[PDB]
Length: 374
Ligand SMILES: NC1=N[C@](c2ccc(OC(F)F)cc2)([C@@H]2C[C@H]2C(=O)c2cncc(Cl)c2)CO1
Ligand code: NA
Ligand code: NA
Image (cartoon, rainbow, N blue to C red; front, side, top):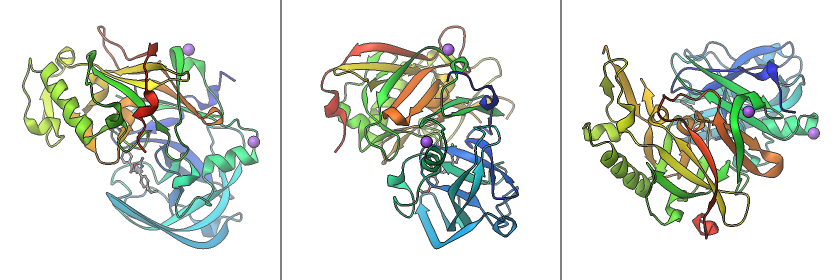
């Protein structure tokens, strides 16, 4: 408890292409780099020689592979993957010293899934069975891990933006990874890591929307999404306020829509004209909340001879998504055992001399249950 040195720095990434952990599958072990995804629930790996893949799972080489004789088709947007289900022995070399038999989807055909130039070959869905494919009987990796071992039912993530890196602490918390205190928000329902946002401020100015809007139709914590995604009506209100706050300088209307980038000469990004963004989350106690605050350092993503950033807040029709934009400010504890998510200021987050990311409480917020969409 509290210290897991062998797991520190076990994540790598390329900016905007997520964070991956090294895993092994089968016997003898086949090493793969695997995207850490709290937004889905399948352990799915490249299993055929797609041109974009550094490597792939070769089931014929594994003495421990068991075929489940079942296929899985997984459309979404933007993309799709198809595969064949089986089980095999899975380990995390820079994780706990255990080996479990997990479900693996062997991806045999995909569209807009693998990224050309990325260094990962599969994804580790760390969310709940309720959103597993094809259905909730396909046990997710973390569920198997907890069933078959003495690993405590929690994991935590420190994503450090900019080549990026971070830490996935499986089975506990490492106190070196954060400063100040952890504050907890309930997991509303075990499918995605669903939370409830109860208030939103831009530079301390409340958006004053019916808080149900902040959670239409859900709000989730998703390490497999780069951006902070906001429901359309909230995004509209959010940019308008950010536009206003940052009107010292003018940017093309396309910029706020992510349709074009914006640049400055090196060493001269005007951070301070940009507002902080605060989400108040439902707390653990009745009528009690806390707030997490992020900087432009988080929502203006590094992508000429100038420093060019993409506006990394965007509209959604699937609800709020707290992607890397949020998570890179914080140490995030997925406390599955207690159905709660902890946030603390991350010991590695990008800031400046004037402003840092913050996690502050307690605040008094009434009618927070009304903020949940049904
Ligand atoms: N959280 C989430 N993961 C994704 C995903 C892909 C299929 C699913 O299959 C199905 F179960 F929905 C589920 C999620 C993609 C794996 C993520 C992805 O490709 C990605 C690309 N660039 C940057 C990042 Cl941080 C991630 C989409 O959003
Ligand atoms: Na156990
Ligand atoms: Na600490």
